[PDB]
Image (tube, chains in turn brown, yellow):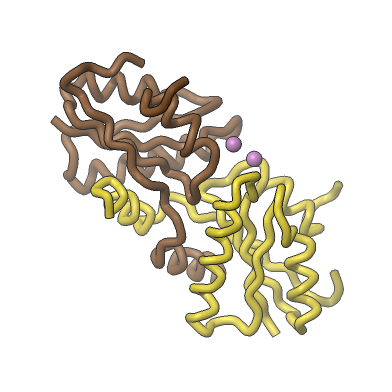
Length: 121
Length: 118
Ligand code: NI
Ligand code: NI
């Protein structure tokens, strides 16, 4: 009844999509949501509309959209909210609700990661 | 003698630089490096060359550059390595260019928090 949709920037190089695919695989391993999907804003498929439509098709009535972005920017304030129909400019049903979440940000766990990377781990 | 340089994409909006500033401040609180600096690839100052120069001027001989990017892309494979002189097109100082964030189990943890509004 609820879906997690991870959305990323998307690049000409495949690394951005590969990242979202691995993250989605890890989320699915946690057994938290019946439905998990990825969408890329640009350059790659699935697109964000395709991901949300796929979640709706599988029976989700609550669509939790998480922007896999480090910081806010024009894509998280404008482009993605527009694709989701949350701001003026994908048909979302009446009984479906989009829950648009916050990006990663300066999380203490990002600091942990950065220190590992700094030491080659 | 060693510096941590965090580099980010940089945006017209201030949020990208503000992120890097907050991360560097948190790193400095860990008391791991003598010298900590940020640089933005585009749109903002400090630029990446400016960040590395400040680290060198403060006495660093080992400059660890960490790309605060989620995934590899043209900026981490070409643009930033070029700005760092690691590819075609510094002193007895050594640049150590590290890997981006990637699909870390801790990113999964963060994402789950964000999914639930935490
Ligand atoms: Ni962009
Ligand atoms: Ni770019």
